Figure 1 (cartoon, each protein chain N blue to C red):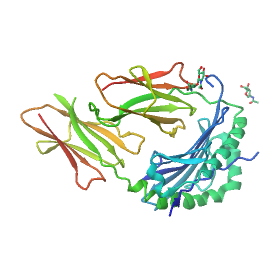
Figure 2: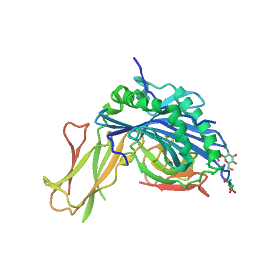
Figure 3: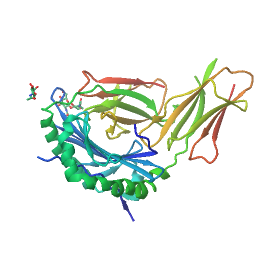
Length: 197
Length: 182
Ligand SMILES: *[C@@H]1O[C@H](CO)[C@@H](O[C@@H]2O[C@H](CO)[C@@H](O)[C@H](O)[C@H]2NC(C)=O)[C@H](O)[C@H]1NC(C)=O
Ligand SMILES: *[C@@H]1O[C@H](CO)[C@@H](O)[C@H](O)[C@H]1NC(C)=O
């Protein structure tokens, strides 16, 4: 049977190129550590770019972040305090255990690996992988390089895959073998690609 | 910055006026799960297999947006009608996978520092605009309460084919092009 994703309730206050605009935002954030052993709930209310009001479960109540929210925090604590507290279980914990566990956290996308040449530099391209955790290693005739190794930051593609580029500072000699070596949760054993001078 | 293994945004809402522009999404570990189309009242999953076992009632998006319409009115007045500042976005173009002659690929335009969340991202091949094979994410939230956004173009890499990612935004005097070639 279909399982329902739940949401954190936005509480309400009491009561164009050159045109002015006005913006408001609400952010409901669930922080999980070791599955659902530690949950932290943080909800934010923001006017334009100024967060003025926050619920943080480590605090236990709404607080004004700036002066704009001084009276907001007193209203929200009267009207939504214990509803928001309970959301830690009815929304964060439920969503992780019942909807992330069977989807987001079972997602495994294996990386693709290709070496190309740009003294000189080898570029190992590691692409289309999910989740983010990965290790990339360079070897030269069976021995691991550690000096001369640099990588780009992790690139988030937005489609639930990442990529990264890992570069090796190298001078090609002889008939050496350079190997790009990738370890990843989708892979029971590493993927390797060899490049020969 | 809070330490955690995982982060769900189970409720990200933005509303602005005038113009009645709003958005509701969920994210997990920084990727979009879905947005509620607020006018059609339906849930639109980032990848279609997300909704095969899981359901999200669009009414939750409607709840959040109505509350935010109300909150916008109150806080606008309390701020003495301080207007938002139009930011200048910045774009980076890169391929989804290594570029290979004749092998279908995806060009990705990442656009950051978007605020307010209203923008145009379009593509040009050899200075001519391209509409087929184009997908665009929702506005995705940043720690500093700006937004980012990605547009995707399907392409066959060839020799000296030339692409530009074109961004127009209120914070830009003229559209900025971000170039790209293999
Ligand atoms: C996004 O693109 C649309 C279409 O190009 C822009 O809307 C047009 O704006 C021109 C600019 O003078 C007007 O003359 C037209 O009447 C508009 N046409 C339509 C169909 O909307 C829109 O302004 C762009 N947005 C931004 C932020 O630049
Ligand atoms: C409100 O904003 C107006 C417009 O800029 C400004 O001139 C005025 O000083 C402000 N008034 C009060 C009472 O805050």
